Image (cartoon, rainbow over all chains, first blue to last red; front, side):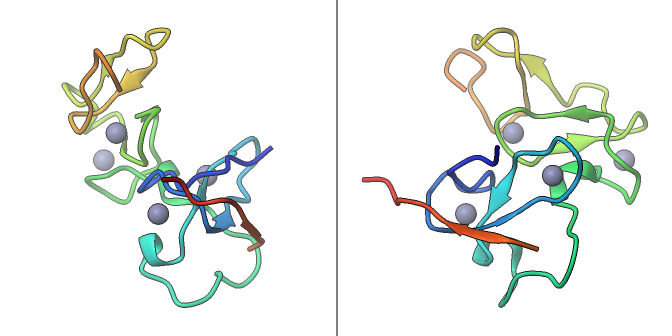
Length: 95
Length: 10
Ligand SMILES: [Zn+2]
Ligand SMILES: [Zn+2]
Ligand SMILES: [Zn+2]
Ligand SMILES: [Zn+2]
């Protein structure tokens, strides 16, 4: 129930897995600027707004970008893949 | 946190 590729860079390898309920995301230590897996239960960066410390309420489905209500305006648009939201790093026609 | 080992691409 965790993905087989790093949500930040998209490649496989050694991945640390998110502990937040229902989150399947996993990441390279290097992509998290870490040397070892965090100690104990860990919450991945997807749940925090890109622009502040608030919890995210809207999410890019293609990378860890996500946004609180204060910062969500204009940040995400539907993509060709079932309408799943994507941030400005992706081509919505081929996310 | 737990880690796992998966295959690299390309
Ligand atoms: Zn990575
Ligand atoms: Zn997570
Ligand atoms: Zn915010
Ligand atoms: Zn994105």
